[PDB]
Image (cartoon, rainbow, N blue to C red):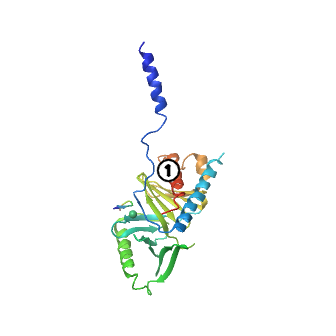
């Protein structure tokens, strides 16, 4: 019959359906710019070390909660990027690269050096400089705006955000303590801490639990939530991590 | 302009 020509064409279709074309690669639509090669090397490194912990734990499956970003605003085109940590400190990444981190009293003023990566300067709000007066006006505006109509909350040093990157599927946060946090369009979140060994999961309804990664991989899924597509989400993390680990010049 | 989940 002509079913032979049909069955053969069918078979070739199934083979081709197992390969890719027009497949999405991670593209950053927004990220803070780092004007230091050394700063990038430190970032790239941290991505590699943390990735290694994932991969080591991936080939090897056969509880302290990390600091996280509770809310954020990418206003990069106007004022700058803002965020709030589980410590309820507020940071603002200014478009020049500098940062002001106001504690829960005082604030840190951060920027980077071509010879020393990141540089920080602690101040008292009492003793704030006149030159940094506009910065804290912007922080004050971000602090109040974020309180009013952004929603989330969390329950041994000062931590700031070195790098954020917004992809279509998720926004990725690189904190200064080596923690990585991923916010998915699924409204599911997870944070990778402690060299890649520990994984934290935050729910759409804001339930958060920290678990060893080996265990979670022993489960084959986060224990509470089956709706969370963990395998795919851990794959995106890995793709995101690897991409950054090679960004060492700009 | 983008942001996290609203209140
Ligand atoms: Cl930007």
Whether A101 is drawn above or below A224: the answer is below
Question: How far across and how far down the image is residue A190, in percent?
Answer: 50, 56
Camera-side residue of A96 and A233: A96
**How many callouts does the rendering have?**
1
As helix, strand or loop, the secondary structure at mark 1 comes to helix
Seen at 59% across and 53% down, the residue is A54
Q: Does residue A86 show up?
A: no
Residue lying furthest top: A1
Seen at 39% across and 75% down, the residue is A139
Seen at 47% across and 25% down, the residue is A11
Label 1, ligand 1: CB separation under 8 Å: no
Residue identified by numbered label 1:
A236
Question: How far across and how far down the image is residue A109, in percent?
Answer: 47, 77
Camera-side residue of A4 and A148: A4
Camera-side residue of A50 and A35: A35
Residue A159 left/right relative to A1: right
Residue lying furthest bottom: A127
Whether A122 is drawn above or below A75: the answer is below
Question: How far across and how far down the image is residue A174, in percent?
Answer: 50, 63
Question: How far across and how far down the image is residue A16, in percent?
Answer: 47, 32
Q: Where's ligand 1: which quadrant?
A: bottom left
Seen at 36% across and 78% down, the residue is A137
């Amino acid at each position: 019959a002509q079913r032979r020509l049909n069955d053969l064409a069918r078979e070739a279709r199934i083979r081709r359906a197992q390969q890719a074309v027009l497949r999405k690669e991670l593209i950053a639509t927004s990220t803070n710019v780092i004007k230091s090669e050394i700063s990038l090397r430190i970032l790239a490194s941290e991505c590699h070390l943390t990735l290694n912990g994932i991969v080591e734990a991936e080939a090897q499956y056969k509880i302290k909660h990390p600091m996280i970003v509770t809310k954020w605003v990418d206003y990069s085109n106007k004022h700058g990027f803002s965020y709030q940590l589980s410590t309820e400190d507020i940071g603002v990444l200014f478009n020049n690269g500098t940062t002001v981190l106001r504690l829960a009293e005082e604030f840190w003023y951060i920027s980077y050096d071509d010879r020393e990566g990141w540089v920080a300067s602690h101040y008292l709000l009492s003793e704030k400089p006149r030159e940094l007066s506009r910065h804290l006006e912007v922080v004050d505006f971000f602090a109040k705006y974020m309180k009013a109509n952004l929603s989330r909350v969390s329950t041994k040093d000062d931590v700031f955000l070195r790098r954020y990157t917004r992809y279509k599927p998720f926004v990725m946060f690189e904190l200064s303590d080596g923690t990585f946090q991923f916010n998915f369009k699924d409204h599911h979140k997870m944070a990778i801490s402690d060299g890649g060994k520990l994984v934290t999961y935050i729910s759409p309804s804001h339930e958060s639990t920290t678990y060893p990664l080996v265990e979670v991989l022993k489960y084959g899924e986060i224990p509470g939530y089956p709706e969370s597509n963990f395998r795919e989400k851990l794959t995106l993390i890995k793709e995101g991590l690897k991409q950054k680990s090679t960004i060492v010049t700009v | 302009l983008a942001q996290s989940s609203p209140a």
